[PDB]
Amino acid sequence: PPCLDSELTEFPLRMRDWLKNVLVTLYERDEDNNLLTEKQKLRVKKIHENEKRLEAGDHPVELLARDFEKNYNMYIFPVHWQFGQLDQHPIDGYLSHTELAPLRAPLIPMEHCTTRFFETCDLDNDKYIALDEWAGCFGIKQKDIDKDLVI
Ligand SMILES: [Ca+2]
Ligand SMILES: [Ca+2]
Ligand SMILES: [Ca+2]
């Protein structure tokens, strides 16, 4: 199904919240780093223990927007971690259309908007998504982009 502009506007808010929450479940499911490496796990623990963390639930988009404003800091790692997970074939700091396939799966919220959203983040039109085009699209500030959280 086609992706309305009205839907496209919510996509990043929905996607960002989803990443934050999926990363939290991995932290809980992990047994002896079978799911997260020690470094990644330690970063997620801080998010999981945060008293102000917005729990998963059905939240109107304006509440999601407010939490990103107030708790911007807990979204930095989730956004980077996801890029690192997809950049694999080959690992080069860019995401091709093929590497984006997992985000086009039925269980992704608004997955019919994925391709249209990414065309939007591709500022230089090379059909690949660089880390900075990725982070920027998800609202991460320029000063917070850090290739080291992608490892
Ligand atoms: Ca790549
Ligand atoms: Ca879906
Ligand atoms: Ca590009």
Image: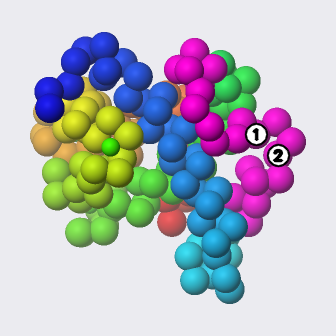
Of the numbered discs in the image, which one, if any, rests on residue 102? Answer: none
Tag 1 near tag 2, CB within 8 Å: yes
Image height check: is 69 above or below 151? above
Local crowd at mark 2 within 10 Å, few (<14), some, or many (≥20)?
few
Q: Answer whether residue 100 is visible to the viewer in this image.
A: no
In the image, ligand 1 is in what quadrant?
A: bottom left
Q: Which residue is mark 1?
A: 53
Residue holding disc 2:
50
Q: Name which residue lies at 82% across and 46% down.
A: 50
Work out which quarter of the rendered image holds the N terminus and state it. Answer: top left
Q: Residues within 10 Å of mark 1 (few under 14, many from 20)?
A: few
The span from disc 1 to disc 2 (Cα, nearest Å) is 5 Å
Secondary structure of the residue carrying tag 1 is loop
Which three-letter amino acid code belongs to the residue tagged 1? Arg
Check disc 2 and report its element: helix, strand or loop: loop
Say which residue appears at 36% left-offset and 47% top-offset: 108
* Image side of residue 28 versus residue 140, left or right: right
* Mark 1 CB within 8 Å of ligand 2: no
- Give the image location of residue 102, x and y in percent: 29, 57
For this orientation, the residue located farthest to the front is 58
Res 127 visible:
yes
Stretch in magenta: 42-64
Question: Residue 53: within the magenta?
Answer: yes
Q: Is residue 81 above or below residue 11?
A: below
Taking the magenta stretch, the answer to whether it contains residue 45 is: yes
Q: Amino acid at mark 2?
A: Asn
- Residue appearing at x 17%, y 58% in the figure: 98
Within the image, what quadrant is residue 88 found in?
Answer: bottom left
Position above or below: 78 against 137: below
Q: Position of residue 34 (x, y in %)?
A: 58, 83
